[PDB]
Amino acid sequence: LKWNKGYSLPNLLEVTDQQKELSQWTLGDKVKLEEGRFVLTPGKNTKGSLWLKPEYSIKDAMTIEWTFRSFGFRGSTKGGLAFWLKQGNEGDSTELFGGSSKKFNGLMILLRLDDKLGESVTAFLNDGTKDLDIESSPYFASCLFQYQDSMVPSTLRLTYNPLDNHLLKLQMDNRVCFQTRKVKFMGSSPFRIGTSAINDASKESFEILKMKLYDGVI
Ligand SMILES: [K+]
Image 1: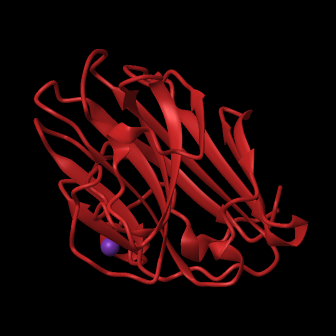
Image 2: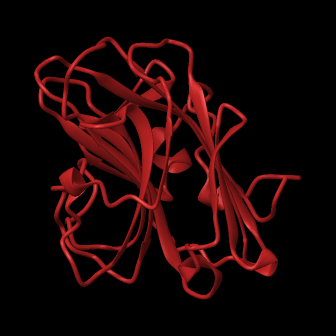
């Protein structure tokens, strides 16, 4: 029922001591805490990221909820916002959406304007051996989802239960985007949790308002 404070963001508005209350988080590149939320991409052609420092090891099951929005720009762009669960590596690349090398081991959930689906959530797996080629449409799951230019936040909820043969469910605003049993690495290995974004000169503002992790399904 209760969230795991050690793997969650604190209430960002209520923060008084930024250094203390964010000690478990790495702020990457241009991300800034501004008037009660993180702005990942505050300027033209900026990138930013938030990563939990400790690796998470699942007990039975887990829920991650990210509350986010994109404000200020609706239209054509290669910019986007990624949510990551990554395994066993520590390169310095930000080539993929301000967040990762094209070659990574884990799960990337991407909000972007896909050349063929348009405004969408697309989910990708990589096993660390190949460069992910995004423009070949190699995602294992997807849904259409409107995110650009809304003050009203959305919530991504990822639930994952190894005990139910690795059922992973991804909901956007409490509506199912996809469900899968293809993602299994989180049941048996520690992994890193984070988010990243990149924009362009149109200054799309990708923002994180809240993040909670729960040590079960809710
Ligand atoms: K910190």
